[PDB]
Every structure is written in C-alpha cells, then in structure tokens.
Length: 216
Length: 216
Length: 4
Image (cartoon, rainbow over all chains, first blue to last red; front, side):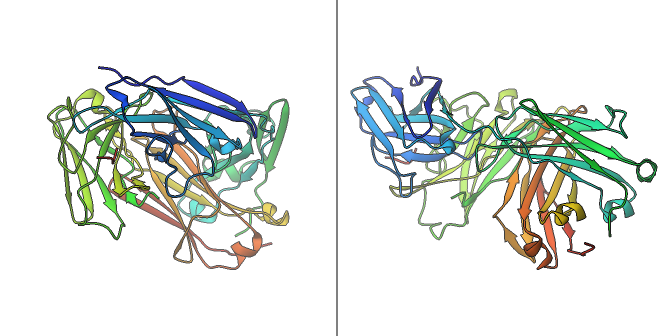
C-alpha cells in the first residue's frame, strides 16, 4: 500500500502565499480527478476546502486554489491570514470505491505580531464558598506566541502546591489562552492578605493580586 | 457546519464494545445513505473505516460496523483493541459542494477510573467591572477521559459569540483540566438574569449558573 | 470522501 506524500510543514509570510503538494500515483492521483483538501484546525472537526482538483466548496475562504500537475496535486493559499494555521490533508480516489489520504502538512504564518497576555485573576464565588470550597483561577489570554509561565504567590511567599496550569490553546484567532488554578480551603482564604498570579511572557511579567474583599 | 452532533468522549476497555454516534440536524435525513466514518489517530492522516452507512473499505477489521436510523448514524467498535484508541469523525455529502462534518469523538481505552468533571463558573470580578470589562470563566476540572463538550447560555438561549474553549490539559493526577471563557461588557452582563456554563462529559451534563448580582 |  501507500499514503500520498505531503511536505510536513509549509510556512509563508503574512499576506503572502504557500502551495502544498499532495503527490500520488497513477492508480489514484492522475488516475482520476478526485482530490479534496482538508483544513484541520489545530486538532478539530476538519473541513473540505476543495473537492475536485480546483473546486472551492460552497463557502470557502476566498482563494484556496487547487491544482493537479500530473500526479502532483497542489493547494495554493494566498492572501495569507493568521487563521490559515492548520493541518492540511488531501485525499484522492484510488480504486474500488475507496479513498486514500496523504501524510499531512502543517501551515505556518510568519509576520504575526507578538502580543502580551491579558491576565484576569478570579476570587472564588459565593456558591463555591457555600458548597464549602475555594478555587482561584488565573486566566491568561490573547497571547502570542504561546509560551507563558505562571507562578503563584501564596502571600509573597510562593505556593507551588495545589496549583494546576494548562498548555496554551489557539483561540478563534492565532492568540492563545491558558489558565492556572489554585485550590484552597475557604479557611486558608479568609486566613491571609493577598493571593497573586504572576505570568511571564517573552520577557514581560504581569502580576495580578487578589484580596478577600470580594462582593456578593 | 458541525450539524453532525458527536459525543465528546467514548471509552471502553479491551474486549468492551463502544458506540460512537453521529446525529444530523439536517433537513436531509432519510434522503440519505452517504454517511462516512473516519478513524483518526493522533499524529496520523484521517482514514475512512466506513462508507455509505454499512460498508467498510478494504482492510477495515471486521469489528467496525456502521448503522443509520432516524438522524443517527452509529459506529460500533465491536470488541475494543488497544489502537482503536483514536479520534473518530463522521461525514455527509449534501451532494457536491456541501460536505458536513461531525464534531469528533475519542476512543479512550480506560486504565483509570472514570471522572466526571468539576464545573466552577466564576463571574466578572468587581475589579474587572471597575475597569469596564466583563468575563466569566468556566473551569472544567478533574475529568477523565480528557474530552468534554462545553456550551454557554444567556437567559436560556445558547451563546456562541465570545466563548473560547481551551484544550484539556493533563494534571499532576492524570485527570484533565479545561477552561472556557465568555468575554463581555458590563452592559451585556448586567442586562441579563442568568448565565449557564453547560458541560457534557460521557452520558453526563453539568450546568452551573451565575446571575448578575451587582455589587460595584 | 463523498464522491462516487
């Protein structure tokens, strides 16, 4: 057997252009005119981008351009937007009723502005406090590039224990979102002055400090 | 769009069978056979394991079976093996131009007890409001297996605009942690009565509500 | 993959 070749990664500058090559075999690609292209957004419910060599499905992003250059197929993305970061796959009909896929090309847009995160800290709410627990939530958001680190400050001494953070995910953007959580007993929470969520990103640091005077 | 409602997580053990399901909203159903199922491992290209409701392609192990009745196609891994563990998707060809995808699933071969998520909705802290910002967080924590559906609601009606959902992170107890957020204005927040964060894990829904109670 |  075999599964179509794709170049594992395809960069381009902003507003520019890239072309990915789904490359097959006489028995599949070049056998028939039935190559579709797929946009699989950083691990997501994938969509169809082309169906037959160069036909843009009923509501596609402006200028996905499909090519079949013998047994090499090509998808040309131009007017480069940030949102084109994805997993690009192709599929060609091979024989008896069935389709063959390709390796999988990750598309990379360059020239994306670096953004420093919006740290929103949270005090626990009444309900949680009634239910008898306290969990604090640092929300880091709209950052680029997606490397951030979260310290917790118990009260100006650190609190390594009871913290839990998340790997940054891409938004309907190409900005990331992350969060830390500190799980506390309410007791512990009446019992002392400040809590702090310190977030470092590309040199910057943003600290947010919360105090027990939450209203409800 | 994802008008093919697919479960968030589907899990079993070796030798236990698992149904994935794929529901259509589609004013379509009946006038239909063309429902194709895809087996997709993390790292690999997507590969079809079912075409036209019940036909697997060449080399699909016997255990995969598809069905469709009502508006529901179903895929039964009949006797679960290790690398049945993958992302699964479904499909429907509204002829040519309109290739509707389902939203995905996951096959978890459990080797950890099932953990239904802790939801913990936090409302626009008084400070953030004092900055004329509005954001409520839906912490989803301690869930296994690490796939979960998240949806929001204002005054009953669902909210789509402004919600960003992170990807399940593995925690220092091999259970999972996600977060959504709804970004708003004090206006929109204050101008309502109740906001649910609604979360779906396997065969479970947790809906937690926050009301605007406006201390400053 | 629909086609067919």
